[PDB]
Amino acid sequence: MISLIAALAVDRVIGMENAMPWNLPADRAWFKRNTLNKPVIMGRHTWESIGRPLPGRKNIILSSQPGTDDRVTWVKSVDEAIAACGDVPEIMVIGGGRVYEQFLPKAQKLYLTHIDAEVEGDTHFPDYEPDDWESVFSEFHDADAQNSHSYCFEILERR
Ligand SMILES: NC(=O)C1=CN([C@@H]2O[C@H](COP(=O)(O)OP(=O)(O)OC[C@H]3O[C@@H](n4cnc5c(N)ncnc54)[C@H](OP(=O)(O)O)[C@@H]3O)[C@@H](O)[C@H]2O)C=CC1
Ligand SMILES: COc1cc(Cc2cnc(N)nc2N)cc(OC)c1OC
Ligand SMILES: [Cl-]
Image 1 (cartoon, protein in one colour):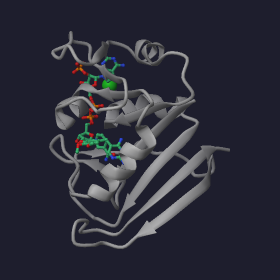
Image 2: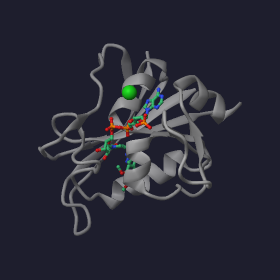
Image 3: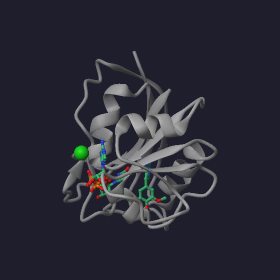
């Protein structure tokens, strides 16, 4: 099983200048929950965004160029990433825009955080047909002192 987990603003925005254009600790909490003790495949742009290994997960970076951090696994292809995760129950693909593009066709599950924010963005979740997917579970949260936007955590499964 391959799964994508991603936070989407109003216009499927996921990124602005190699950062998420919002601050939702409640999202980073939901991200940690569903990825922990599973392998994560991220693109080199996302690695640099996070800027440190994600504890309690084998970290797998996609980069044509050679590695620059001895604490994480590096791979130069999609097939190498996928192989690098090994015989596991679930592979979590955690960004960014170009990695999502490549993995979404392969993906069985979506872990979507829908954020009530119309924010300028250089990077968007790839398009898809909701025809192709069926809503499994969702959870709505109001904005609060720490999370300036309302948000909905959704899970979808292929057919
Ligand atoms: N909203 C959300 O849920 C999330 C937000 N983001 C946002 O996403 C943005 C980053 O997305 P984007 O700019 O598309 O980049 P990525 O984060 O997908 O990383 C791009 C890099 O990945 C490497 N790469 C990708 N595919 C391959 C491949 N098949 N073989 C080899 N290397 C590969 C390349 O590295 P190289 O240059 O070494 O060749 C490429 O330059 C940021 O703004 C970030 O904030 C990211 C995570 C989640
Ligand atoms: C743990 O912090 C980060 C996590 C992510 C990936 C990510 C974040 N949120 C969700 N819902 N899905 C994801 N795949 C991306 C990040 O930066 C772009 C992070 O830095 C704050
Ligand atoms: Cl690419």
